[PDB]
Image 1 (cartoon, helix red, strand yellow):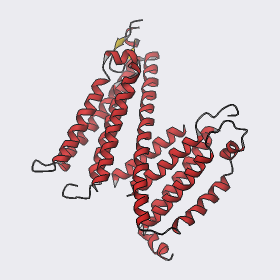
Image 2 (cartoon, rainbow over the protein chains, first blue to last red; image 1 turned 90 degrees about the horizontal axis):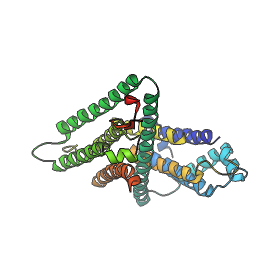
Image 3 (tube, rainbow over the protein chains, first blue to last red; image 1 turned 45 degrees about the vertical axis):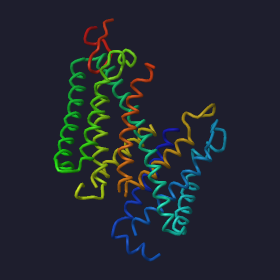
Image 4 (cartoon, each protein chain N blue to C red; image 1 turned 30 degrees about the horizontal axis):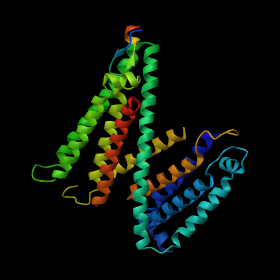
Length: 315
Length: 16
């Protein structure tokens, strides 16, 4: 029931997302002008955030399924969609201009928080994957599973190295763009440490199922984040598929995260709040130095989270 | 059992 409802909400969220994306097409521009695509997407995202936030607050402190709030959580879909459409229509009725920039800042904030929570989910996913795979290797034919892990981890490292080489070739030059070099080098050194720190005998003694596979996954994600970071730099002299890949990891993370009378198996309110932050992130992704700072800070906090998740239990 | 400090982590399958 919990998983089914979470998947329902994820599916409707993705439906709203694809709606927003299709509005942006130049074909739809003439129809909208009868009341461009960027403004329509802004309105849709604002409606998404507003209604998701109000449901989140409504489901605050859900204690039991007998409470009508949980029953609504399990149903009343017609009412949900009606509220969605109603707020969507109201979204346009707000005047634009400065409020647009206010919502732009709000969306930056939400995207930052969402990338934080998404990386938390990603590290949890990698830990679980590694644990299950190593257990299976221990039980059955050790050699086959071992070769599997080795191959996948080495392939992920290979992809990381080759993409970093592409970054060297394209986004950096000896005559300038020293900031790009600095970002590349700092990310490389931190991720290399994250790899090395996975091999500390004390760490393994405190984290029996830690391994290189999750380290490689985190490194690759970080390199992707870096590529997106300079991808959005307005300066073409220094500077789409990155955005599509971001949406793909969005879908993956949301699906995995989605994957009663006595107590709630999960915080419904915090679930709705994460959905809202996801909507805000979608807004931003569909669209200057501040963005670069946001992305690099996201990379830094990601690697900080990795170090924390590896060390804190020892503390 | 004889666990070890292998790449994938802490286990004894290779030396069970």
